[PDB]
Amino acid sequence: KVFERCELARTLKRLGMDGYRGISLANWMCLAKWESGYNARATNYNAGDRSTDYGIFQINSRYWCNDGKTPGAVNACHLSCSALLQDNIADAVACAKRVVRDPQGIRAWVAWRNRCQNRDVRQYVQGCGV
Ligand code: NA
Image (cartoon, rainbow, N blue to C red; front, side, top):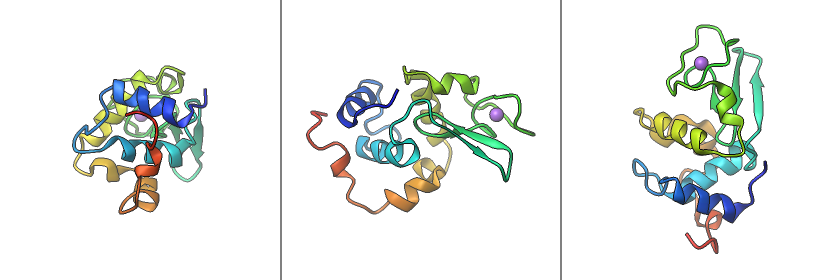
């Protein structure tokens, strides 16, 4: 499933993402937009280190979920990476909440730094009723 902008915004709000660990909803929308284009089944293989990025927030298999093929990896979210590819994004959200609970916060994703940090991210939630 590929979410539409406002549908995703309302879904994230219902899942308790607005202001989670100081991160506004528009920042989460900006992250999702650049990481996957709001595509819940998106996957990206990183040939360089043999890890794979999964789902709407493109969560990496080295530290967050288990896919069995990533060398010396851990499973901090205690989830199969398969769980991060469902149309129902509850598990991906729970795992993203775990990711930001680390020191770096939202900065854990390089794409956030490149295209969201210090920018006007209001456009991502404008008119969605959130
Ligand atoms: Na892992």
